[PDB]
Amino acid sequence: EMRLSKFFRDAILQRKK
């Protein structure tokens, strides 16, 4: 869908994992 939602997905969401 979006490559930015793919970027931050590993940036913001890997903090909370």
Image (cartoon, rainbow, N blue to C red):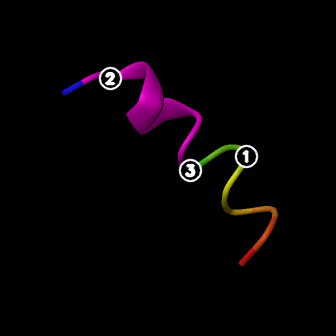
Q: Which residues are magenta?
A: 2-9
Residue bearing mark 3: 10
- Classify 10 Å Cα crowding around label 2: few (below 14), some (14-19), many (20 and above): few
Q: Which residue corresponds to the image point at 59% horizontal and 35% vertical from the top-left?
A: 8
Q: Which disc, if any, is residue 3?
A: 2
Label 3 residue SS: loop
- Asked whether disc 2 touches disc 1, contact meaning CB atoms under 8 Å apart, the reply is no
Q: Amino acid at mark 1?
A: Ile
Is residue 3 on the magenta stretch?
yes
- Residue most toward the right? 15
Q: Amino acid at mark 3?
A: Asp
Residue bearing mark 1: 12
Q: Upstream in the sequence, badge 2 or badge 1?
A: 2
Above or below residue 10? Residue 4 is above
Relative placement, left or right, of 3 versus 1 is right
Relative placement, left or right, of 16 versus 10 is right
Q: Looking at the rendering, in which quadrant would you find the C terminus? A: bottom right
Disc 2 from disc 3: Cα separation: 11 Å
Relative placement, left or right, of 14 versus 5 is right
Disc 2 from disc 1: Cα separation: 14 Å
Label 1 residue SS: loop
Q: Upstream in the sequence, badge 2 or badge 3?
A: 2
| Image coords of residue 14 (percent x, y) | 68, 63
Q: Quadrant of residue 1?
A: top left
Instruction: Give the total number of marks visible in the rendering.
Output: 3
| Image coords of residue 7 (percent x, y) | 49, 32
| Image coords of residue 5 (percent x, y) | 44, 30
- Asked whether disc 2 touches disc 3, contact meaning CB atoms under 8 Å apart, the reply is no
Disc 3 from disc 1: Cα separation: 6 Å
